[PDB]
Image (tube, rainbow over all chains, first blue to last red):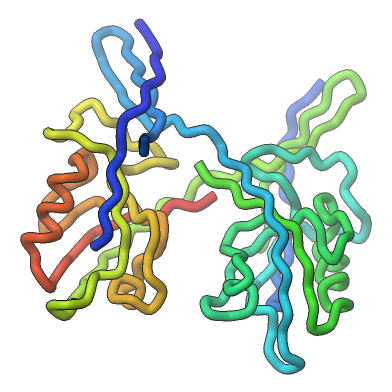
Length: 15
Length: 15
Length: 124
Length: 124
């Protein structure tokens, strides 16, 4: 068992 | 020592 | 550099990735100047109290008693940067964090065409 | 009727009174028709991922990966009922809850001038 925090990258897109 | 749940009345107002 | 905090939680070989964002508490001062006949363009909502509720305890989730239920778009408050869900901290320099609804509304009406509000936006 | 739920915690003669209001999950459908030159009027933001993230787990606070980071007031999406912070659930009959940004964007673009979406709003 484990609990881990991670930054997942995000993108922005104007539509 | 106690943890109690209570409702408080809320009002709305247009300004 | 654009990114979001998630939590990876695993136990018994079952996995779960959930969003895990820190509370962003953003305090701002909004200054509202309306004409005699227009309204400030918002609906205020919160706890009724004939006197301040001293035992109220602010949390990141819920910093104060009175908040913005709705803001009319293109209205005065909207243009002044106020948005739905902002919590009122000060009204015309007066601390309202623990103040009953009737009294906060009073303070607002007293100001006439001018309204100065310190608010906080909580997002996650 | 119009009332909020507050928790009253007390221990050793100290009191706190805090509000613990649950998240509202409000699903809606939007139909968007634009002109060739105009935009839909929104900025989409969400996790980059080549393939859907199977272990992603929707929570009340965060139902899905791609969300509306802003919506142009009186733009096409706004008129269609979309608001800032809406979570994308389905895009042209494709489930996108767990889907990475590039692919969702690709679906939106394959649609041309028409976009039909299930989205979810969340508030506290």
